Amino acid sequence: AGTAKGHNPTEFPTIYDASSAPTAANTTVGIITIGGVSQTLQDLQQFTSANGLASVNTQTIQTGSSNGDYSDDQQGQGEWDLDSQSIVGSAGGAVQQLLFYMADQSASGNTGLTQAFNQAVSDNVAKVINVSLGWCEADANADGTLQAEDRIFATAAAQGQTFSVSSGDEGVYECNNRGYPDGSTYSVSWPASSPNVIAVGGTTLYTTSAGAYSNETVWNEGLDSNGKLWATGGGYSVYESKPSWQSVVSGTPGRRLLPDISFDAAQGTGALIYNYGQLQQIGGTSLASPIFVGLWARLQSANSNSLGFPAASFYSAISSTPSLVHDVKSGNNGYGGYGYNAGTGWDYPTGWGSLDIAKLSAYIRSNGF
Ligand SMILES: [Ca+2]
Image 1: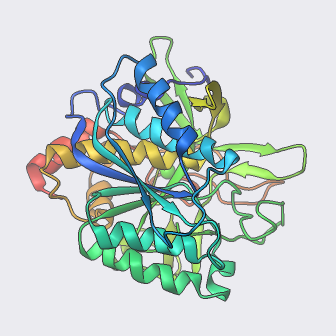
Image 2 (image 1 turned 135 degrees about the horizontal axis):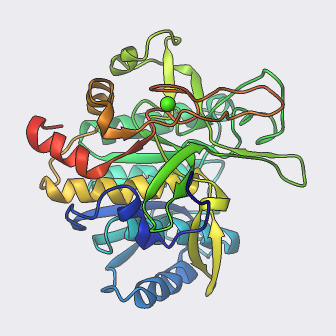
C-alpha cells in the first residue's frame, strides 16, 4: 500500500498527525554535534528561507576547552543538517531556540562527546536534546565511556530533560565492525541502550498519493556495496538492567530493551536535506530521532514544558492504548534469515512504532504524562 518516496521535513507533521498541535515555538531544543556547525547554519538558513518560514534562533556552544577544535567536520555537516532541518520541520516550522552543543574534536578518547552531553545537562536550558550518534555499547563499556555518560543522562532524566538517541543503522550487527552480517550474533548501540534516554528506531514510510500516512514497515535496506547492513538498531543491552516500566513487554530478558519508539528511517523514504547547498535524500535512525525530537517539542510547548522524562509514561500509555501508535508488524532487522522480526505490539526492530501525535496529545490532556 502507498508509495515509497522522499519527503520534505515540513511534511512530517502531516504524516505523524501533528498539524493540530502547537509548534515548538515555546520549547528550546538541543542538538549534540561533533565539531562545528558553520556550514550547517547556512544550510539551515536555506531550509527556512526556501520553505517560507520565520528564521530560527540558534546558538553554538563550545562544550570543552576554549582552545579545543570546533572546526567543521565536512561529513558531519550532513548529520547536523539532517538533525536541524528534520527537527524544525517536524516541530511545525518553529522552535524557541536551537542550541548546538559542540564536542571538542581534539579531546582525548570520547571525552569531547562526554563533555558535550555534560554541558547540555549542566546548563539545563534545552528541554529536548537530539543525539543522532552511536557505536557498539561493548566498546563504550570497555573504556569507561558508558559509565561516565550514563551518569550524565541519569541527571538529565531526573531534571526532566529528554535525550533522544538514534537506535543504530547496523540492524542487529552493531558490534561486528559496525554492521557486517554476523549470523545469530546480535548487539546494540550506545547511547541508545541507556535507560535514561529515549531510543528511536527506524521505519520504512509509505504515504498515499495525497501525502497522507499509509503504512510503516521495518527499516531494512540490506547490504551496501561494501557488504554492510543498513537497518534499524534494536535488541537489548547486555549491561543495562530493565527499567521497571518495560515489564509490560513480557517474555523479554532483564535488560534495557530498545528502541522505545520509531519513525521514518529508510533512505528510500527519507528526508530531502540541504547539505552544502545541495539537496540530498537522507535516512537512518539519524533521521528518526530528530523527527521524534521535533514532534515531542510540540507536545512540550502544548504543556508548558512541564512533561518529564517520558519513558515510563510511553510504556504504560501505549501498552494500554494501542491507538496512540502506528504498530509496525512487517520486516526484520537482520540479514540472511537472522535478526529480530516485527510483530504485534512492542518488538525489537521498532519498539512501539511511531506516535500519532494528536492522539497522544489528547491522551496527555486527559491523563497527564
Ligand atoms: Ca510492532
